[PDB]
Amino acid sequence: DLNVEIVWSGPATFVFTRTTAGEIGILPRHIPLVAQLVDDAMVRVEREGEDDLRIAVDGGFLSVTEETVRILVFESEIDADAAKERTAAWGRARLRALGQI
Amino acid sequence: LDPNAIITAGALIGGGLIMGGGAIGAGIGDGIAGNALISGIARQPEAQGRLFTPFFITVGLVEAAYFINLAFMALFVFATPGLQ
Amino acid sequence: LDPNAIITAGALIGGGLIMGGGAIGAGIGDGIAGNALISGIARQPEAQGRLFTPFFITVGLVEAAYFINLAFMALFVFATPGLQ
Amino acid sequence: LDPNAIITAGALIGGGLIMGGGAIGAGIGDGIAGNALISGIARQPEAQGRLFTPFFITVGLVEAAYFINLAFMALFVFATPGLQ
Amino acid sequence: LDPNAIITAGALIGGGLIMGGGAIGAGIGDGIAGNALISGIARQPEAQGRLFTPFFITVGLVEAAYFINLAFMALFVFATPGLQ
Amino acid sequence: LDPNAIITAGALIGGGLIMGGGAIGAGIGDGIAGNALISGIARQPEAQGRLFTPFFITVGLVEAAYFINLAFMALFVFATPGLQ
Amino acid sequence: LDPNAIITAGALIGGGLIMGGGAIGAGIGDGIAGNALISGIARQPEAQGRLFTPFFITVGLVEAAYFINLAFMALFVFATPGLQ
Amino acid sequence: LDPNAIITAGALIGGGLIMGGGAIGAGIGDGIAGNALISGIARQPEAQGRLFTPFFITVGLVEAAYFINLAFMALFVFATPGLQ
Amino acid sequence: LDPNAIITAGALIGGGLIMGGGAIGAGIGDGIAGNALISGIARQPEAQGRLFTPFFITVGLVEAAYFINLAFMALFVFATPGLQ
Amino acid sequence: LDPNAIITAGALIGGGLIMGGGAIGAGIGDGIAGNALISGIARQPEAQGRLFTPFFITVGLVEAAYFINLAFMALFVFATPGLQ
Amino acid sequence: SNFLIPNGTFFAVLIIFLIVLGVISKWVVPPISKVLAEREAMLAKTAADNRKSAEQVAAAQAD
Amino acid sequence: VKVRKPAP
Amino acid sequence: MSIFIGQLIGFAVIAFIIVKWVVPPVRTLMRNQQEAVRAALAESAEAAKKLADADAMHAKA
Amino acid sequence: NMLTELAGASALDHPLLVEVEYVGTLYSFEPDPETLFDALLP
Amino acid sequence: AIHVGHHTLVFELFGMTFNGDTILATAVTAVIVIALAFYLRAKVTSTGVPSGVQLFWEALTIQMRQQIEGSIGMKIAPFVLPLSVTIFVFILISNWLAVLPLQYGGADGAAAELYKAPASDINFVLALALFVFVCYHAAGIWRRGIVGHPIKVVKGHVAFLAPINIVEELAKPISLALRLFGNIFAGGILVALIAMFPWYIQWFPNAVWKTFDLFVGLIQAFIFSLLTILYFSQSMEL
């Protein structure tokens, strides 16, 4: 497992997101990395036998270290009705997080 | 010795060269274009539909040469120029 | 000597060239496409599924050349055109 | 052996080499240029309109090198130089 | 000039060409796929396992062609088409 | 056997080799340079104006190598050295 | 002309082609795999231990093909099929 | 027949091979070096002055080989070793 | 016509093919390995020493084949198999 | 027919093959190494001198093969092994 | 003789293919499309029923 | 802006 | 007949490989899909029952 | 921290940047480090 | 003795030759496909647990519908789905029926196959490829009109490359056929070549090649289906 820290924090098994270069998935021993999340980036965290956390992010920055994955920015606290330039990006972020896409 | 035999052997060798060169070119070019397409899809899932339009354009050109070669190869082995 | 012997030797050499070119093209194109696929999977493992579709679109577009060559190669060696 | 037959066989082999080389060059160069175009469109979806200009220039060179060869092959095969 | 001698010489040359092309294609394709595999394992060591799924598929599509050439080279040098 | 026939066949084969190699080099080099140009323009559109300077140099160093060979093929085919 | 002489010349040419193709494939594939390994080690000094397992596999697949060619080349030049 | 005919045909074929290899190498190497130069200038416009010195070191090497080949080809075709 | 003359011509052509393929493979593989080494040293100043470990392996694999081929070329050209 | 003529033609073809392969390898390997050098200097201007240490090594190795081929080509064309 | 030359078999094979296509068009794909559409509609109805139960269990207490 | 490199 | 015997042995090997390493995984996928659709059907039935119960409770209240 | 790592790898020519301080396995930057530095320094 | 070609059961009719072996193989494949289809028609259930045959058929339909949706709207081209699925199943069954042990010795030392994959015959591949060719060209005629369609295919995505475009349009059918042909034709030879080994050595290479040929046939059916769908999409746009 790898310690994910959204700045939520805790162990996880997989971390999916979408940077400027493209979609990236991080596993426990990924190489050190520094990337910029896309404007409407969505971060999915898969834990050992728990529901995946689908966080919406604005102006994020991913940093993978030998120990932890730190995201420098949830679907439960998002309303679809209000979710439907940067304003468009944030709306798209909520849409992606919810699952409407 | 039959002149037609020599001409036909030369035509067969030339057609083989044409088709082998076309094969190399088509295979490597298509592999390269497909590598580009696969990377683009892996990095931008929604980009797939947008990527086919340029991709196949490339393939078109890459295919053209090959089949053009094929055509000439036929002319070498089925209607051999200079054959008596 | 026998015209058919010369023609058959030429046909064998031409078919060898055809198959050599086809093998080079197929091997290198398949390697490049597999490189794209493997890099895409390593970058983001869960994309594997959606990558297998374009990959086989690439592989086919490559393999065609090779196998097309193969067909013609058979035509060279098994039913030699212009074999007196 | 009729000298014309030897000259024609040599011309056919030479033209086959010409077209094989042209096919290899055209296929691989077009594949590489198309890889560049596809990657650019993948990273910059709005860049398509501006990319087609340089891309074709590349093709305009590659294809040229191919078609020039296609011309000379014809000269080799249809009007064979030195054909006594 | 026993015709079978010319047939066998041409068949040996064709088989040599077939193996040359097959070896080039197999070696380069395997090297490229291995480059992708090594880069992926370096980037994501924990994805190693599943990364073998595409790699072998690529190695399946490359080596196959090689051995296919093998099957056709043996033919050329053991059951020569058109042999007299 | 007319010596001029053998010499002309050899000259045609040599010229075919010359132009095949020239076409391979020109096509692949132009493709690679165009790939660099296309990627550079895609990354930053404003770079276009300044990018055509090195590009034309690269193509200049590629096409030249082609055209020289082309000229030499003429020597081989039209005024064959040592034609006897 | 001794049939064995022509057959042996063809066998030597075929074995030369076999080694040429094997050499090209082995050298280029090993170079590419080593490029991947060197890049991986440069990025991670401690990844070396885990990077030899895939690298060797790649070197296992490439070299094997080359060595297979070697065997057949011996067969071509030491127990020539079709010799008499 | 005249031995000079066979020797001259062989020399022409060898010179054609030399030019084919030289052109392939020169074109592809110049393309690769120019790709590096174009990418470097695109990323760092100010680097245009600094990048030329390595580039000319690369091209200078590449062209060297090509021109050396040319010299030897001039030896093969105009003053054929072993001519008689 | 002396049979040994034909056998020696075939052996010379085969050895030339052996050395040409070996040279292509060695040159391109060393170029690729050196590209990796130069990039790695550029990215990390202190990495130089350690990087020479995998590098020497890659070159060791690339040169081995080459030199092995060289050996066999000698066998072709100095102790010709099947030569009477 | 003079056997020395056949041997000389074979030696000329073999030497042409050797030089063609050597030139291809040298050109492409030097291009790749120079691409690495130019890229490294573009990223790290401070490394303008450092990178020349590995670079030469790489070039050395590449050039080595080339010149070795050249040497053997001389032995092929000037002191042909097998004249009789 | 050449195996690459077409034959009358080209017609015969075509005919067979055609009838197979007909079957697949008239007894495979329409039923399968209907089944898939019904399954998707059932999933949508399940979601709607869950939401309606959730809102009724609240409204009843409210009213 | 801290930089973890020696001064030039 | 000899080549027939060899080919039959080869086919036996093929069938052994298929049953050993191909049948189990595909059977597992078939079971997974069957159980997923069965669970969907059960979910729909229990959701209909839940809506009926909610309607009954609302009418009572 | 991330800014320090990007500054080390990236050329120090950002207009906003021009202060700078110097003190005595690498980090991979998914795009070029220059773009990340430009987008992060603000 | 390898006996390339040499179709058996050949018969004449209406002044045309017919390769009886390929007709029989195609008929067997069609019978298998129709039997599967009818076995489905008697087991389709939208309310119960689907049978394995229903799972297979619906997996094929879902994959092909997904491909169409990605390329061109289903409402735009509903007819493409049945064509793609039938092509896929036909080619897959034809290729996979060769795994069965129908190869024997013809008493001359040359192997003879009781069942040979029909795609190893130029007529079969030509039939499929030309039918698909006419189908998507007629679909393009309907979509863009009788006059517009040829104009658009000649112009292509970029008008000034009209010559190449023409070649491309001729390359689509041929590449569709020959590719498949080769893929199967190669097998039809390799097994025959493997027949020259003694049984105690023949068993192993034959097993390896047939196991790989299973994947080859699956991949070839998949590629043919996707390429047909994509050509339909290219021919039906704007």
Image (cartoon, coloured by chain):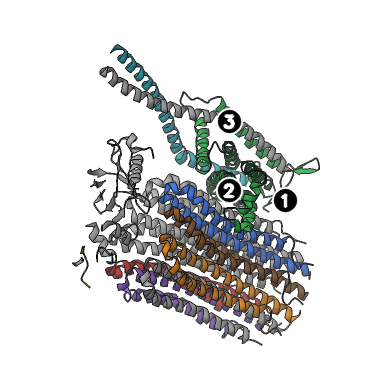
Chain colours: B blue, D brown, F orange, I red, J purple, L yellow, M cyan, O green
User: Could you tell me the amino acid type at mark 1?
Assistant: Ile
Whole-percent x, y for residue K20 in the image: 63, 34
User: Could you tell me the amino acid type at mark 3?
Assistant: Ala
Between disc 3 and disc 2, the foreground one is: 3
Q: Are marks 3 and 1 in contact (CB under 8 Å)?
A: no
Residue at (64%, 75%) from the top-left corner?
A: F15
Label 3 vs 2, first from the N-terminus: 3
- Structural crowding at the residue carrying mark 1, measured as other residues with C-alpha within 10 Å and reported as few (<14), some (14–19) or many (≥20): few
Q: Which mark is residue O37?
A: 3
Whole-percent x, y for residue J12 in the image: 60, 80
Q: Report the Cα–Cα distance between label 3 and label 2.
A: 38 Å
- Structural crowding at the residue carrying mark 2, measured as other residues with C-alpha within 10 Å and reported as few (<14), some (14–19) or many (≥20): many
Using the rendered image, report if marks 3 and 1 lie on a common chain: no
Q: Nearer the viewer, residue O124 or K26?
A: K26
Side of M18 relative to O30 (left or right): left
Q: Nearer the viewer, residue O226 or D60?
A: D60
Q: Is residue D51 above or below residue O35?
A: below
Whole-percent x, y for residue F21 in the image: 57, 71
- Structural crowding at the residue carrying mark 3, measured as other residues with C-alpha within 10 Å and reported as few (<14), some (14–19) or many (≥20): many
User: Could you tell me the amino acid type at mark 2?
Assistant: Trp
Chain letter behind tag 2: O
Residue marked by disc 1: K5
Side of O97 relative to F6 (left or right): left
Does residue N9 appear in this view?
A: yes
Residue at (68%, 40%) from the top-left corner?
A: K14
Q: Which mark is residue O199?
A: 2
Q: Which quarter of the figure has residue M10?
A: top right
Q: Is residue J50 above or below residue F48?
A: below
